[PDB]
Length: 472
Ligand SMILES: [Zn+2]
Image (cartoon, rainbow, N blue to C red; front, side, top):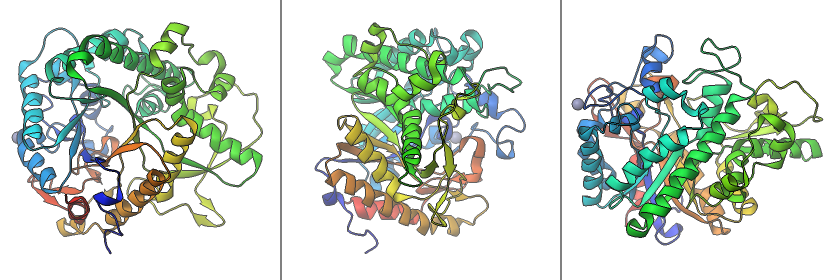
């Protein structure tokens, strides 16, 4: 049947299903309601940076329409909603003066969600550093971010935490490090070649270290000041795409494992075990910052659950490990990407070139975390695929590839859970077609279509699929 045997009964009791957005991608009102600019506002307003020179000034205008969108997600039988708070909408300069109008918006959103029986899962940060902090402090290159982020987090805990019980600090710090400071294609556009400056061999590691230290500091503040009264939880969201050895050779299996360690272990080994992966210590050496014993003890165990954003999988081919002049975080892995095996592609691509449709990658990732890291509580915090630009409304709505995508990926997640993986929830990226970063409005990830001329919402076939699967 079109559900393929899936329903709430096929998952654990009290398993959480939700949808996901982020502030800059859906809110709009980017320069209104008292919001200060983020590094993404500056980046997107520069000609050439985003597809079609588009930006998030208006986006889906969820700022004005949030009750429509909450009504819709309730009608589709979701239990929860993952969204982010824009740091610069609360603190336009990232520190100092509070924008009360911004505070009121998130109060209103949170209160309506609760009124409608949808649990808020709230991210503090989703790529959108206040531009003032980038300019004044140098953003995530500066260890002072720990203090700056903790003060912002403290405000959010105090202001919203009597109602919000499920927090995340960051979203995919690996992607910030990779695209912001290795390749230099996302803000602040730093890299060895880059006009803005940078060093692709050192800066990604500095940035990741500062995310880990800031996460740990924010959680320490939660636990020492707020947790007794509020009784909520705080985690982090990490991307993890699967790596499969191209062959059973020792060198191909070692390559796939190196890729896992440089991708997810970079954050998970510190968060679970209190140190960076051994292979990273061995290869990156003095370019990898060292936690002091005290810092390592603050980072270890500092995530109450691990959010995983899972989309795709790649084959990995190995090589003899060589002594090499450092060039970049990416080159440090000493692996070779491969997208076919035995003459067959690993899967077909969605609209995004990096997004190969590989449902068994979901099982791969979840099983791996279960087996390697002592089966921590995991929440799938994003999973989904995109349609291309320029389709007709009805073409967007008949999204049979996305229906197949969710049925297959959820069957694979179910397989892992039935084998004992401690997965507590699953969140579809995205509730709505939205501003997809460098792709702007040319990539459509939503289970709900948004007409970007009229701003009208129309649920796609995949939205009705969820509604059917999730009925109580
Ligand atoms: Zn509006």
